[PDB]
Image (cartoon, rainbow, N blue to C red; front, side):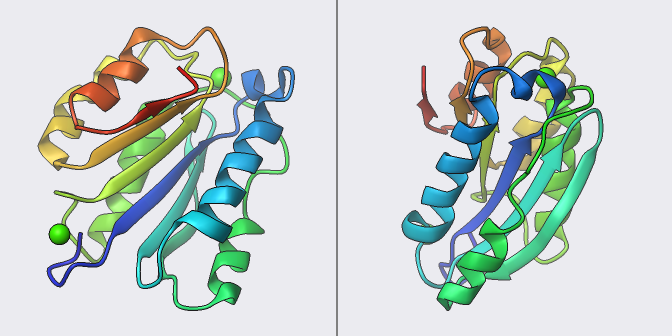
Length: 161
Ligand SMILES: [Ca+2]
Ligand SMILES: [Ca+2]
């Protein structure tokens, strides 16, 4: 959070090729739309990162004060799935997005992914150091175990699992 009590949240959204399977990308978009249009509270700072093998900042931190802010974030949810997978690239990019304004300690990441990534341990240290809270939504059934561990070690919530 900010020093004055505003939530800091970065959506980290898996748009990799595996997400083309089934309805995974539609479920990601549904979850992202619910979060952006209904759940996140007035006054929160909110950023958005997509990732395949590399991270793409869809939005720097912007504050939710109007329905236009929700809408402008929701219009940037990924339309298509392609490329490789690096959860860690997406999380590092989220940390950079947050740290343009604020510390990451007590900030939140909403990680929407199928979890099919066996290199997650590679950012454990950075994640522990960040103090961020990683919420994970597993959108497939073959999620690595390190996805859960991202949540467990940061105090985040786990869902679809
Ligand atoms: Ca607080
Ligand atoms: Ca993938």
